Image (cartoon, rainbow, N blue to C red; front, top):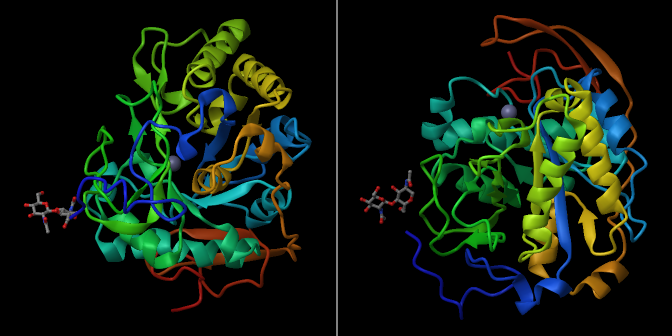
Amino acid sequence: LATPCDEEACKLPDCRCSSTNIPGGLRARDTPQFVTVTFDDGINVINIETYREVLYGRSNSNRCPAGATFYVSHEYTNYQLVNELYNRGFEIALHSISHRTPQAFWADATYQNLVQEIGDQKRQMAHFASIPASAIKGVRIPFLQMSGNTSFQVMADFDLLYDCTWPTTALTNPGLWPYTLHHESIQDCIIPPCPTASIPGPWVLPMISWRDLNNFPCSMVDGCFFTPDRTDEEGWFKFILTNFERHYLGNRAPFGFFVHEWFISSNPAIKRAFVRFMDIINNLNDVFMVNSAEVIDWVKNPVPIDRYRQQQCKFTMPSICRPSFCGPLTGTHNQLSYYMTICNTCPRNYPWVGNPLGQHH
Ligand SMILES: *[C@@H]1O[C@H](CO)[C@@H](O[C@@H]2O[C@H](CO)[C@@H](O)[C@H](O)[C@H]2NC(C)=O)[C@H](O)[C@H]1NC(C)=O
Ligand SMILES: [Zn+2]
């Protein structure tokens, strides 16, 4: 059971307490503003068109490729398209093998449940997308449903670096910065149960809630209730930038744009506001559209804007896809049949929970 923070024991780069103070003792105006654009759930031939259109070719003002985090769930994911996203410099993260309903399952999952749903997905993902296992570091639990200590224990066991499942509404201005779980967390638990054990090793990357038009909090853009009309491009542009300014003109805590792709392609006016927002921050000299792992990397060794701008761009190790089209595949638990596009040789059976590489019978 974790104790309150021993500000003398908890030291970078290995340990940090839950706090709204800027890492490294930096002043806000010397602190880079990070933006983490993220997309949940399965990668397929439809939503990849949105990702190519609004993300490809972008760069930050330091000429590094602008990043984004894909919390990928396994079912109906085209792993050749995952490989493509990885090779354009975007981060591939875990969102479970099954994404199974109901949400209540994830609140209670056993250690073994999350080993098989998340821990095993790391090698599943590296295998079928043919990307370095070391590049897989992030976790978002389905339905934003925390699992107490359990998910963080699994992360420690499988060298996953950070979780981005845990929103805050009380700690948004000044915003709560990432922290480790060596000690007790001050973060509010909107979606219980939250971890209270001392679990050294993984990081919490809080989802700092947005504020909607009536000041109600929302964790994801497509979860905001009081919102401009879907056809009102200018209203959505002002809505996005107002939430962004709360960070940029505040303590500069990482600003999230957490969405499902459906919300972007279903609403062309929102997509246009979204594109304009990205165009603006790509032209700002102290704002950076990055992968979520790069936020943890900065918190671990915080540097002022001027030195951050001198750091080398992320290194994206190229990894070729040798594509295979596989099927019909079936599983022992699945009842369904499947076809798959992967960057490896075809498995004998459908990869699933308890058989993550489709290898066994
Ligand atoms: C997570 O780990 C902590 C630390 O072991 C667990 O803490 C227990 O919490 C209950 C109250 O819910 C206390 O009655 C126990 O005494 C605590 N144990 C210890 C050793 O202090 C916690 O229950 C675990 N599970 C969850 C879901 O948080
Ligand atoms: Zn999801």
